[PDB]
Image (cartoon, coloured by chain):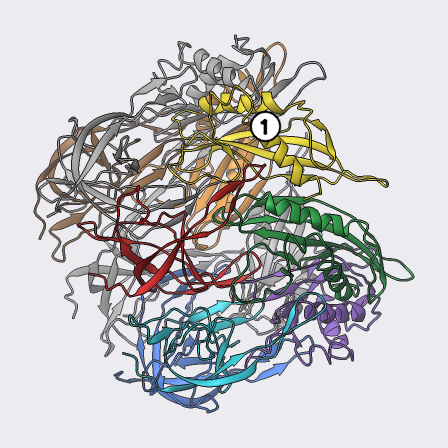
Chain colours: A cyan, B red, D brown, E blue, G yellow, H green, J purple, K orange
Amino acid sequence: RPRLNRLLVLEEAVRVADGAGGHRLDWQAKGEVWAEVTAGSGSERAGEFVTLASVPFTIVVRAAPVGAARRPRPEQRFREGARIFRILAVAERDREGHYLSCFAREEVVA
Amino acid sequence: RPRLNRLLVLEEAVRVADGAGGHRLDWQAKGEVWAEVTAGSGSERAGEFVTLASVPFTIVVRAAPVGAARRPRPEQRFREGARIFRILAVAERDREGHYLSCFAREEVVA
Amino acid sequence: RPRLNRLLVLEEAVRVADGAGGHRLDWQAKGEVWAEVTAGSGSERAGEFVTLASVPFTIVVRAAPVGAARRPRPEQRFREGARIFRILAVAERDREGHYLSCFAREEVVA
Amino acid sequence: RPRLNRLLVLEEAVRVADGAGGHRLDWQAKGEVWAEVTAGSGSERAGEFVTLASVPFTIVVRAAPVGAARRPRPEQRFREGARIFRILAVAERDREGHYLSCFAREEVVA
Amino acid sequence: RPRLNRLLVLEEAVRVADGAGGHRLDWQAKGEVWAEVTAGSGSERAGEFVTLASVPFTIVVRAAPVGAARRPRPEQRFREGARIFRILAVAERDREGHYLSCFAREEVVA
Amino acid sequence: RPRLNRLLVLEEAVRVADGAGGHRLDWQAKGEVWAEVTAGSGSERAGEFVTLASVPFTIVVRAAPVGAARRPRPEQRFREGARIFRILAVAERDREGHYLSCFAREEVVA
Amino acid sequence: SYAVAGALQAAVYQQLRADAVLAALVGTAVYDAVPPGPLAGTYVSLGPEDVADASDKTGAGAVHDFVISVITDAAGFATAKAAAAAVSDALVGADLVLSRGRLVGLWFLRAKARRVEKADMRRIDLVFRARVEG
Amino acid sequence: SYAVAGALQAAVYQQLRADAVLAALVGTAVYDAVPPGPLAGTYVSLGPEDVADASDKTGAGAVHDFVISVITDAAGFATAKAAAAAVSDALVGADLVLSRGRLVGLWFLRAKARRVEKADMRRIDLVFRARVEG
Amino acid sequence: SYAVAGALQAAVYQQLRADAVLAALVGTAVYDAVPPGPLAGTYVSLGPEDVADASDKTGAGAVHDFVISVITDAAGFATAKAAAAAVSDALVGADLVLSRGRLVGLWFLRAKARRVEKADMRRIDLVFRARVEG
Amino acid sequence: SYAVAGALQAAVYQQLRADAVLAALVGTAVYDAVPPGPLAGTYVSLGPEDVADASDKTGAGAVHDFVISVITDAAGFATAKAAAAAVSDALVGADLVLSRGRLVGLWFLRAKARRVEKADMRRIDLVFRARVEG
Amino acid sequence: SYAVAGALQAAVYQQLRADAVLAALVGTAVYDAVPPGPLAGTYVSLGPEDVADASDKTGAGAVHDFVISVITDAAGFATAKAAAAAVSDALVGADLVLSRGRLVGLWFLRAKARRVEKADMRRIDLVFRARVEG
Amino acid sequence: SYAVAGALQAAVYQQLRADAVLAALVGTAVYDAVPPGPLAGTYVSLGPEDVADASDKTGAGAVHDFVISVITDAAGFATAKAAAAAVSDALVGADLVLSRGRLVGLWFLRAKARRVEKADMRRIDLVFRARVEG
């Protein structure tokens, strides 16, 4: 069972809609979770005009019902200091349902 | 052998045909199954204009003959609350034929 | 060694040639084999205009010389009731030559 | 170490050159080898206008120096009755150099 | 736990901006780290007009906070003599956080 | 640790430059190494107009400093009789640094 | 697409499945949405149009170049020709009735015919020009 | 893109979600940025324009060929037609108000309609020509 | 495709396998659907036409640009030329008999020739223009 | 590229990061080479030109069709429009100073706008024609 | 392809391997089918033509645009130029003898030259127009 | 390619590595075949021409559209411009000496400039038209 050791400031953006239909994100902070962060095989990835450096980072937190504040939705991102971990998906790692796998990137521009 | 713990409301859509040849789906509920849901490696996937977040979710239920109500056909989808699991295929997991692997997505827009 | 438990009605089509060079298939039945059907990882596949649901289904039967009726050629298909298993290839699974791996699809339209 | 059980009639084509630069193949027979034939995962493959059924078939024979008749060059093909096994490459399977892996197809039109 | 045996001169380039917006790199040396260099499966890769020979080279060093000099950012490269190891990403290999996986290339023109 | 048994005549080409900027290769011989040659999964590969037969052939020799004659650079090729092994990359297989993995092709036209 | 396109696919679906030929040659397997089941395998499909915006100052219309594909699991595709021949016999110069506006001419355009996948299935597209008037 | 493109997408978003039809046929699911949640599945999307730089010595303008796609999870895409018909009924000859300059004519162009992925989702692009004057 | 396309592929298959040359140069290996077995390997194939809709007010016709490919397992493809030469000697100016309508001219068009796969098999397409009259 | 291209990208970078708008709308994130760090995410990029060689007997010049892309991590890309509007307000009819030769007209060309990857990032290219005289 | 194509590749293979230059510059490595062995590595290849059907009422002919590629394993491809120069010196205005009909002019067309794979091998195609008369 | 192409790449390589600029801006890193070693990283490359066969009844010539690419490992590619500017300053209106025939005009054509891979390396092609006379 996972050994949780990092403090990840979970962050959810409020979506202020603009006139054209596109929302504007704020990334106001949410309450902090505890998690383990297990790396994957990382390599740099061609962005737009940026040679973005990415690593897979399966993050494991504890669980909650889907209408609770403690669930990381894939809308949200983690942030440890200045290292933003995006959330690709959340997937309910444990069999009994105690732990959630998340999926991250840590795309540093490099 | 699989330990079944989730209650999944199986749902089958009746196909009201429109004038052009396309059926209109309703997704009326069917009776509930018990299942285990084992996650796969998940990552977000480029939809149409949506950055859809998907995870593989091999779902295992019990079996039935193919002309029975209890078989999940790949027409149908599961739904646990508001988390719709589509069915990709059903594949008869067990050797003796007691259990069926299903294959899901859980495409949340994110 | 494989435990054979399913009854698969082997089917071979006679090829009535039309005037243009294309044969017309009939899929008259052939004698029934016994086989095991081991599933693979299944997912739905984009057909023509159909979202076909496929699963790999390595089918294992017993063997025969190549000029015998009991060999499933890849011309032929299996059929268990109304579930047609196409044959991709036959590959002589056993070392001593007692068993043949087949390779199937079960493309249900879904 | 491999258990050799099949008799494969090795075949080498003499190359009668035509006027345009293209050689014409004959596939005259060569002496017979003993080999094991281990299947791979097979599936049908899109040919030209033929839905060719292929299986990988790593064939293992004994070895020889490269200027000997007993080496299967990748020019050559095997043939067991009417089942022609093409040779993709030969690769010297054993550490001490007693056995050669070959690589086949068995493309039946199907 | 990794056995560190190579001395890698870490190098960081100062970015003198030119008039057009593009920075000019210098690759001034930084302090030397100790590391292990574990090779991957290497093969030559098509460059621009160069047939560049690359190998994966997961390099493992010790860790530091992200605002420290001892962290290899993916901006930087290693250099052992005249063998420059680029850095693809850094990924925090250890569970407790003592060791960092790096990811290299060693693209020699060949 | 690898058991070295083959004698591979290492070959390095001197680059006589022509007037247009392209060097002309000679492939003069260099001193002979001892190596093991471990095959990979081989299959024929579409060349230009040649159906080239290739196999991966991870070759393992002993090591040297990078400015020594005994290092196979990826410029060079091996040759055992008339079987030329190109060098894709060299990758320092051993942890202590005694052995080098090379990477070959053996592209016979077939 | 344009405003008539809601009624155009509806009416060309209704002229299909009413021709006597292609009812004895395909059956009931003429659709846009596939009825899930066993996938009979000698169907046609009528969905992908595109518009070429032929309009006016006073009023507006559309040029719907809709594609009706013919898919066939038979070994040869001489079976797929006569089903596509019964498509084209049913639609060129149709003069049918629409729910939004009307069409003025349902002509014929390019009709390619090839093997889609693994050379097991054969797709015969049939592009028909539908100049409708809104 | 050009200077008017900040105000053009804003105003064609405001003429959408104000038509009575497509409000009873799509709902509130007209957007550029997708609101994350359950993904309702019969939305439209209004983002990808491109400019064809029709300008002047004295002043300058733009030809925005913006694409409004219609995506629909229904089995057939006759549902997606009338939603796209309500797009085109809302926008050709619009004569709306911009924040930077004005437009002079919001015409109609090509509007293809196909299956994007696995043949489960159906995309109906609708290219509209927006000759704006800065 | 068009109504004549059911009879056109049937009649050009019958003029093939009746020429004396290409019967001693290919054999019985002229088909659309491949007879499964050992795959002889010097066959031809006659399936992919497309139509260019040349029609009338009174009546309608078609321009079938059908492709007859020549596939050959031989090392060089000088063998595949004379088999394709015996195709073209058999079909240009054919004046054959159809079951639906008639053709008026079976001309010749582009005929590319290349290696399809792994450079082991050689495909010589031969596009023939078939202006048929329904 | 041509001899002026060393000075052209330098001068259009200097007219950028001096406009007051796009300095309060992007910031200091106008570059060719990306400053590594946290990747702010609402930058522009000015690198890919191409030349259309408009020259003379006596002297020679160039037509630099340089692309300035606008990339934006925001949910919608109405934010990316006004940043691209401030690009185009800064560059059409620029009349700037070069180090090798001079330019005679910095016009405007096509400016497409789309989602590059996973539909998370939005690229607005802006092609500007730069007829320079060497 | 056309009837002359059986004899055309045969005769242009015979004019090759008879020129004194390219026999001291390539050797015996001029072929269509590759002789298996060690793959010498500075060969040429003469297979892919295509026909442009230039014909008549009375009689018929062909425009064979055959490709002769030059492949070279050398580090630079100045070696591959003079071998391709000896191709073009041997074939433009050839006036050779065919077995079926005759050719009237063997002209020269486009001749691209690039790196095929991993930038180790260099392909110089040489398209020659062969107007033959059947 | 054509007969002059053996001498053309040789002479444009000799006019390069003799210009004083691009010798203090690239160095000795002008080549076709790459000298293996450490890969310096601000080189140019002169190999891929293609011919446009401009010839005569009496005599024959060629239009070599040869590509000289500029590759640069620097963060921005303002460094790669002045190296490419020193290419174009060295070659347009060259009037050099060939070994087979002569050239009559070495003009300038399109010169695109982009990021090849991972956006780390920048390729500036420079197409030059070389009308040579054999």
Compared with K47, H58 (above or below) is below
Residue lying at 33% horizontally and 35% vertically, measured from the top left: D52
Horizontal side of residue H95 vs G13, given as left or right: right
Residue G15 appears anywhere in the view: yes
User: In the depicted view, which residue is nearer to us: J102 or K21?
Assistant: J102
Residue lying at 54% horizontally and 17% vertically, measured from the top left: K102
Horizontal side of residue E30 vs D81, given as left or right: right
Horizontal side of residue J74 vs E69, given as left or right: right
Percent position (x, y) of residue E9?
Answer: 40, 85
User: In the depicted view, which residue is nearer to us: E48 or K126?
Assistant: E48
Quarter of the figure with residue E102: bottom left
Compared with D70, E29 (above or below) is below
Which residue is labeled 1 in the image?
Answer: K93
User: In the depicted view, which residue is nearer to us: A10 or D47?
Assistant: A10
Q: How many discs mark residues in the rendered view?
A: 1
Task: Point out the image quarter for the N terminus of chain J.
Answer: bottom right
Residue lying at 52% horizontally and 49% vertically, measured from the top left: K114
Q: How dense is the environment of label 1, judged by Cα within 10 Å: few (below 14), some, or many (20 and up)?
A: some
Residue lying at 14% horizontally and 58% vertically, measured from the top left: D95
Percent position (x, y) of residue G113?
Answer: 51, 29
Compared with D89, K32 (above or below) is above
Question: Identity of the amino acid at label 1?
Answer: Gly
Residue K107 appears anywhere in the view: no
Percent position (x, y) of residue E3?
Answer: 26, 84
Chain of residue at mark 1: K
Query: For numbered disc 1, what is the local secondary structure?
Result: loop
Task: Point out the image quarter for the C terminus of chain J.
Answer: bottom right
